[PDB]
Image (cartoon, rainbow, N blue to C red; front, top):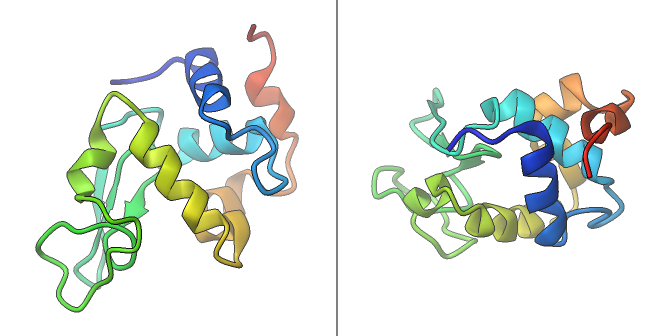
Length: 128
């Protein structure tokens, strides 16, 4: 599914992301925009053999099992395919564990480079 901007904002808010660990809703929408272009089916292969999955591009090296990343961890205890669903619940729940591990939203490269220190509020402007 390819979400609309305001559609995704409302979905994320319902799942408890607004101000989670101090990060306003605009941050999560901005991250999703530049990680996946609001597409739940986005996948991207990394140089080390791992793969990033879903709306927030979660990595198979640490967080999910895809059966093809030798010596990796499955800290969110899920198959990586569950992160590609039209239902964002699994992506949201795993993201909460990632952002709580000490490094905050710096775990997402696109957030660090394109959202951090910017007017992230603009991403939820006009939405109900």
